Length: 146
Image (cartoon, rainbow, N blue to C red; front, top):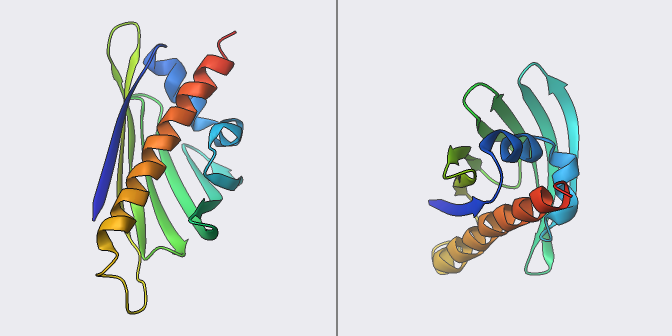
């Protein structure tokens, strides 16, 4: 299944893009994220270790992001961790002197026994998570803007 969040940020795309790329600087404004560490940095891609909290227990994964500096987009995919699949794109679109940020996330989480019964709740949780990742980026861009 897939989730997508969309958010307008009052700042030029290039600036919003660059602030999202500095994940470790972004991390303090992601309230649902407990730990985010960049483990590897290479050319236009990094590797990072996420620990997030949903509903009191933690979900952990490693994430590879490929950064497209030219076109202000990124692609990410988890090769290992708690998700069978965790991937998507951040894109930063011009909307005025500002940025329409679009975050798309395809995930698959296998849950013993209850995976179909709680499919919609899981969905909503993943919706809140990406909406919050974006509201947290809003708050980064404002913080770094003073």
